[PDB]
Image 1 (cartoon, rainbow, N blue to C red):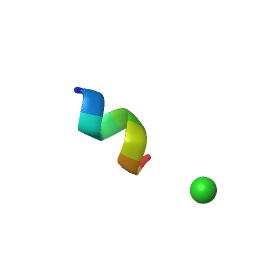
Image 2: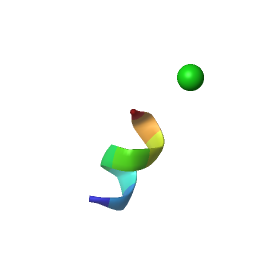
Image 3: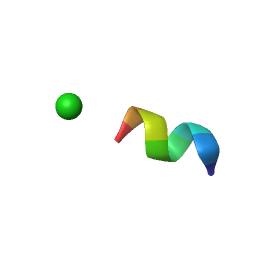
Image 4: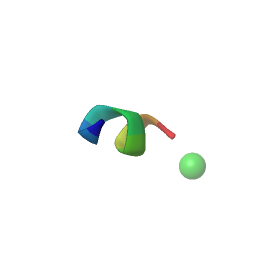
Length: 8
Ligand SMILES: [Cl-]
């Protein structure tokens, strides 16, 4: 979930 936010 933390990577999801950063990538987005
Ligand atoms: Cl961006």
